[PDB]
Each structure stands twice: as C-alpha cells, then as structure tokens.
Amino acid sequence: GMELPSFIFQAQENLVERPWGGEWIALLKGFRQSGIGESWEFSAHTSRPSTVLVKGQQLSMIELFSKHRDELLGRAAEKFSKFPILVRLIDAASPTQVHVHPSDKAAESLGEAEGGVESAWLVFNKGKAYAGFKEDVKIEELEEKLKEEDFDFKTLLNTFETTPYDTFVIRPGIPHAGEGLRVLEVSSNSTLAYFFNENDWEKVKKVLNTKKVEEFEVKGKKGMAETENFGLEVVDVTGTAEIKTGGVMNILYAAEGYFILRGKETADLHRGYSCLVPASTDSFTVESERGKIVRIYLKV
Ligand SMILES: OC[C@@H]1O[C@@](O)(CO)[C@H](O)[C@H]1O
C-alpha cells in the first residue's frame, strides 16, 4: 500500500480553551487570543478528532485511519489496532491542579471506556514541572489537606525548573502538574485524568502512587524521551538533513525555524505546525537555515 503522500497536514486547527491557558498557542497558530490551553495535533480521539488534508481534500483522522491504517502504521500495524497516540501542545501558563493517570489495568478495573495513559513531555521554555511525590505520603493525610481551601499539592512533588527541550516521562500512577510551562505531550490515545479534588478522589485513591519517586525516574534525556510504545526526538537541522521513519507512522513538529520537506512530493512546515508522515514513506529530507524539528515515532 502506497496511496498516501509523504506529508499530511491538518486542514483546520484543533484548539481547546482552558482557564489556565495563556497566549502561546494562538500565537504559534498565527493569531492573538488568551485562554487556549491545548492544540491537538492529528487527534484521532473521538471527543475531538482533527481533520486533515490529503492531496488537497479534507477528511477526519478517524476516517483516514479506518481507510489507511496498514499504510499509516507500517511495521506497527500488527501491534496497534486502535490509533496509538494523542499529540498535544499544552500551555500550562497558570498552575494546573495535581492529577494522575490510570494504567490500562486500572482503567479496565475502573470500567472506563478509555484505556490507560503513559506520556512523554518535551518542554519548550523555562517553567516548572512537578512529577512524583518527593517523600512517601499517606492517602489519609492527603485527604486531610483536601479540607483546606486551596492546599498547594504541588509542594509535595518533585519540582523541576526546566530549560527548553528538557523531557519527562509520566507513567501511570505518577502525580504531576505544571506552571508557566509550554510543552509538547505525546501520550496514549486517552484523556483519562483524575485530579486531586473531592470529585475525583475515589479514582485517585485507586491509581495513585503514594511512594517517593526519585528524579531520575521521571526525567528523560535532553531532547529525547520514550515509552515502550512511542518516542520523540529533537533533530537539529542546519542545511539539509535526511530523516528515516523506520517504516512506522511519524509526526513532525516544527519547534524552531522554517522547513522545506522533500519526500515523494515537496512541502513546507512553519514553526508551530505539525506534519503526519505515513509509514509508506521510508525517508525524506528536511531543510532549514537553522531549525529544530521534533520527530514523534511509534515503537515496535
Ligand atoms: O495557586 C494555584 C493553586 O495551586 C494548585 O496547583 C494546587 O495544587 C491549583 O492548581 C490551584 O488551585
């Protein structure tokens, strides 16, 4: 199967308004607007599917995947029967509340319609990431804190003062939050998240890792992180660089600079935008005066 072009673009922006969102995302997408917390890039999530342009014609990621699944996934086609990932730009400008994701096992046990969530984070600025308890805690003592008006639960977590392109891997059960933080978050194709509040507390108790987590357990390498199912890497481009898909679906995000893309056809990519590369493209070149492009890939 090789019906698809090398480079598939979103037809329209897929943005999410959030009270904690600032101005960064709208600005990436060429306009001025506060209160945008998220941009969903090539979402095949049923709550919020992206729409794409294939050779100039418009369709949903969901349609695209049901029709072109084997070609899109390539060597990952046997491993994944549903669309494997969700890619989001996140502008956590105001502090988010502490939350936690279930594993596949926990989500199934809780009877959720969605699966578990693992995620890899690529940070773009100097902000604060919070991940894992810095000491052992007791569920009961966390519940005492819920009684207070607005106990800062982030004070109980490892605090990371970031620099651009720091990475994190947030595993199921790990409590986390961000503040003044611009981030690319590649996760499972699931949005299950339980916040530290009365409404979600019964779910939190069932999935929360209450043990001390060491910093090395949540920190990735500079510009590079992976789970067992997917990964991301920052490619520094000065001039022309050849990029290999590995015969699996890739997504490219232009973090800095302007790129000319040359595969089966020629295209370009502006800072703030993403490109979907089907597995049927073995390799292609990207060209930039000096830029940084993020390659997101499936692991098989
Ligand atoms: O000061 C902001 C407050 O702190 C928190 O992060 C608590 O963990 C909440 O998001 C917000 O209510």
Image: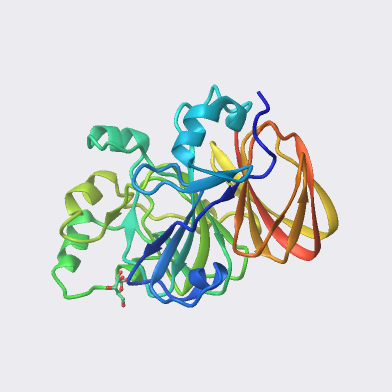
- Place of residue 168 in the rendered image (x, y in percent of width and height, measured from the top left): 53, 56
Q: Where is ligand 1, by quadrant? A: bottom left
Q: Is residue 278 visible?
A: yes
Q: Residue at x 48, y 78 (%)?
A: 32
Answer left or right for 115 relative to 127: left
Any part of residue 300 in sight: no
**Residue toward you, 158 or 10:** 10
Q: Residue at x 32, y 72 (%)?
A: 19
In the visual, does 285 lie left or right of 51?
right
**Residue 127, above or below 292:** below
Camera-side residue: 161 or 125? 125
The N terminus: image quadrant: top right
Which quadrant holds residue 222? bottom right
In the figure, is residue 226 to the left or right of 106?
right
State the residue lying farthest toward the front: 57
Measured along the vertical axis of the image, is residue 294 above or below residue 265?
below
Where 264 falls versus 41 (above or below)? above
**Location of residue 299 in the rendering, given as x and y in whole percent from the top left corner:** 60, 35
Image coordinates of residue 78 in percent, x first then y, are 54, 21
Judged left or right of residue 276, residue 109 is left
Pinpoint residue 91: horizontal percent, then vertical percent.
Answer: 46, 68
- Residue drawn at (25%, 33%) of the image: 109
Instruction: Name the residue rendered at 38%, 52% in the picture.
Output: 174
The C terminus: image quadrant:
top right
